[PDB]
Length: 31
Image 1 (tube, one colour):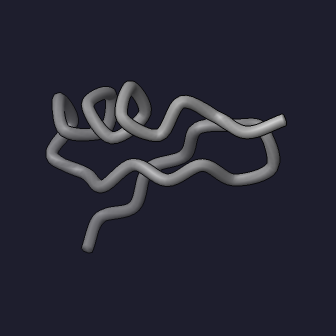
Image 2 (tube, rainbow, N blue to C red):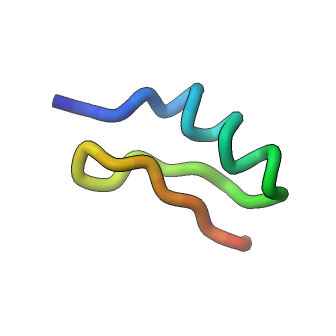
C-alpha cells in the first residue's frame, strides 16, 4: 500500500539526503 516513511527518512539521513515514499518505493533527494 504505502512505504515506511520514518525508516526511509532515516535511510536517507545516513547519506545526508531527505527520504520520501514514491510508488511503494523509498527514494532520496539532495535539498
